[PDB]
Amino acid sequence: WNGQLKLLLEWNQLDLASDEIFTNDRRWESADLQEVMFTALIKDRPKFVRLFLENGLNLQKFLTNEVLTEL
Amino acid sequence: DLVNFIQANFDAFGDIQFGKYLRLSCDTDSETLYELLTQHWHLKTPNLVISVTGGAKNFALKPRMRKIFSRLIYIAQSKGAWILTGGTHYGLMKYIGEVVRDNTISENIVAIGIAAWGMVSNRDTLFSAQYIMILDNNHTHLLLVAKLRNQLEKYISERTSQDSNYGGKIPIVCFAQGGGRETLKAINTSVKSKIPCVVVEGSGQIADVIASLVTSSMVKEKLVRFLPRTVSRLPEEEIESWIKWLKEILESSHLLTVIKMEEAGDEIVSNAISYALYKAFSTNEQDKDN
Amino acid sequence: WKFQRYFLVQEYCNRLNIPFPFVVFAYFYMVVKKNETLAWEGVMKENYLVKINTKANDNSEEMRHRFRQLDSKLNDLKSLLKEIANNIK
């Protein structure tokens, strides 16, 4: 799941990612998003940020001291 | 006073305020439970809008689903209807709790949530023991113990009501959105009681399957298309059970109302619920010719 | 004018708020001696965002999407009819 999501994120593909990755057929779990979420903040792709926030991500949990320090 | 009665009716009850909570037994009679709840906790409800969602924590919040459920909560508040839900603090349940909080911040909404005692690990037995840490925080009358909820729903439907018209029977509509097996079983058992159920085909995989349905090969193809992983992981025995449950569901076509994807107007949930209740009242053959 | 009115009103409210001829006493005495709202704001923010979304969606361009869906359904029906005809023969 993680590699497929990363590949889809490499290009600006919103609807394809929503349909294929978050179809709900296979549970993805919210904690797994963190890594890719960080990349979305560096690639300057707000729509994937919206996807991650709407798909169960806890933004406050993501903004850990280490994460903010590095960012 | 009330606690003393509860001691004999049920002991081992914990009230938490940060939010009343109770310990439920299968042998517990729904009639006495409803009588006590009306006596001390809440008032008689003109309507009951139950929600069926997969017990799995994983969920997806689409904008259309969010708007639909916000409209549902608004309608429930306007009509003062009870809401029955699993209440495990995940996905749709968490969104419902947040919506209830937002509505109440801006005359009260009942969000009774029935869950399983075993499924939740933390124990905070009692007087008003309060603990933090699965359970939801925004629900008002969560209680811990499928069969119990159906029994309570049928008892409430049988109970006569002096208001809300509907032939002295409370609407008690059943609402089911999303994809799952337990939601299939809940819809089937609700249909067994003739309660009108409304479904949304926008997101729910099994909900979309049923919406598209309205033979065995067709059902298998639809569920494979909409549940590839579930179909592949599901055993051979479970396939026959699912097929029979869905076929029995399709037997009562009139009760099952569906929401169309084309509809995008503000008033969609109210129209669907009203149409379902009208179908149920007209086609029941009892006090329908009036 | 409204901006300057705010400035002057704040200036008057900020000082001792005493009549001019009787302010010396205040000077001498003072020298000698001397989240519900945020939740409501968030709810209104959500309502405002929903209103903006409704204003944007008021375009009413869904007719083309409905027509495309109807055309796809017609094509599927035609394919089913062709399959039935092939099965017959």
Image (spheres, rainbow, N blue to C red):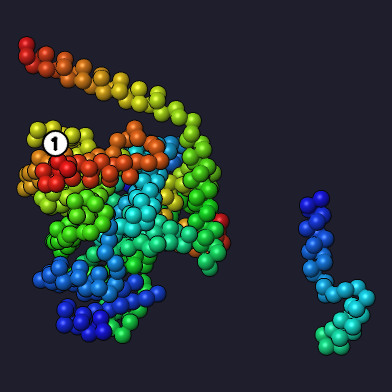
Question: Is residue B184 placed above or below B108 in the rendered structure?
Answer: above
Q: Position of residue C38 (x, y in %)?
A: 55, 63
Q: Nearer the viewer, residue C46 or B156?
A: B156
Name the foreground residue: C71 vs B269.
Answer: B269
Screen quadrant of the N terminus of chain B = bottom left
Name the residue beneath numbered marker 1: B219
Q: Quadrant of residue B206?
A: top left
Secondary structure at badge 1 equals helix
At 26% from the left and 54% from the top, the residue drawn is B164
Residue C13 appearing in the image = yes
- Where's the C terminus of chain B, which quadrant? top left
Placement of B94 over or under B223, stated as above or below? below
- The residue sitting at 82% across, 55% down in the picture is C4
Task: Provide the chain ID for the residue under circle 1.
Answer: B
Q: Nearer the viewer, residue B36 or B209?
A: B36
x 35%, y 22%: residue: C67
The location of residue C40, given as percent across then percent down, is: 52, 60
Callout 1 amino acid: Val
Other-residue count near label 1 (Cα within 10 Å), few / some / many at <14 / 14–19 / ≥20: some
Instruction: Pick out the residue farthest to the front.
Output: B290
- Residue C86 percent coordinates (x, y): 11, 14
Q: Position of residue C25 (x, y in %)?
A: 90, 83
The residue nearer to you, when weighing B275 against B120, is B275
Q: Residue furthest top?
A: C89
**Residue A16 occupies quadrant:** top left
Q: Is residue B12 above or below residue B72?
A: below
The residue sitting at 44% across, 59% down in the picture is B102
Q: Residue B127 vs residue B220: left or right?
A: right
Task: From this view, report whether residue C9 is shown above or below residue A20.
Answer: below
